Image (cartoon, coloured by chain):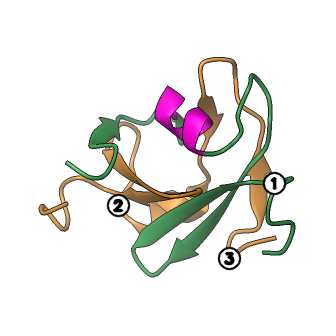
Chain colours: A green, B orange
Amino acid sequence: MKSIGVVRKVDELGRIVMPIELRRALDIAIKDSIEFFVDGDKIILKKYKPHGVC
Amino acid sequence: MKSIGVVRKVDELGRIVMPIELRRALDIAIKDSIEFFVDGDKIILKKYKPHGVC
């Protein structure tokens, strides 16, 4: 149970379902843009347009 | 371009495709487990089995 407290089980390829919370928190509509970071044993997500920088 | 430097376009619901990098990073096999955190304008991912705690 994290901030969103939601867990997903991978499709197969690694495709999962990010929640409305993510869309709300960020700026997601239907196709948007999410770019990820990986920190050791952690993953990070951002909307591409905002931030701009890595 | 983040650590992975890959960006995804949402399916419609918010479903996107997390990469093999994430599977390698954590412990993803086919269904595995990914639980996310949201920090202001950021998202965080973990495999549920490891960590245990939030």
Q: Which mark is residue B3?
A: 3
Find the distance from the CA under tag 2 to the CA under tag 1: 26 Å
Label 3: which secondary element = loop
Mark 1 belongs to which subunit?
A
Q: Is residue B25 visible?
A: no
Q: Is residue B18 visible?
A: yes
For the magenta stretch, what is the residue range?
A17-25
- Residue A42 on image: x %, y %: 43, 70
Q: Residue furthest top?
A: B12
Picture residue at 70% right of the left edge, 23% below the top? B11
Q: Amino acid at mark 2?
A: Asp
Between circles 2 and 3, the one closer to the viewer is: 3
**How many other residues sit within 10 Å of disc 1, few (<14), some (14-19) or many (≥20)?**
many
Find the distance from the CA under tag 3 to the CA under tag 1: 14 Å
Mark 2 belongs to which subunit?
B
Q: Which mark is residue B38?
A: none
**How many other residues sit within 10 Å of disc 3, few (<14), some (14-19) or many (≥20)?**
some
Mark 3 belongs to which subunit?
B
Q: Amino acid at mark 3?
A: Ser
Residue A19 painted magenta? yes
Upstream in sequence: badge 2 or badge 3: 3
- Residue B45 on image: x %, y %: 42, 57
> How would you classify the magenta stretch by its main secondary structure?
helix
Q: Is residue B12 above or below residue B47?
A: above
Between circles 2 and 1, the one closer to the viewer is: 1
How many numbered badges does the structure rendering display? 3
Left or right of residue A25, residue B30 in this image: left
Picture residue at 78% right of the left edge, 36% below the top? B9
Q: Is residue B28 above or below residue A54?
A: above
Q: Which mark is residue B27?
A: 2
Return the residue at label 1.
A48
Picture residue at 53% right of the left edge, 42% below the top? A14
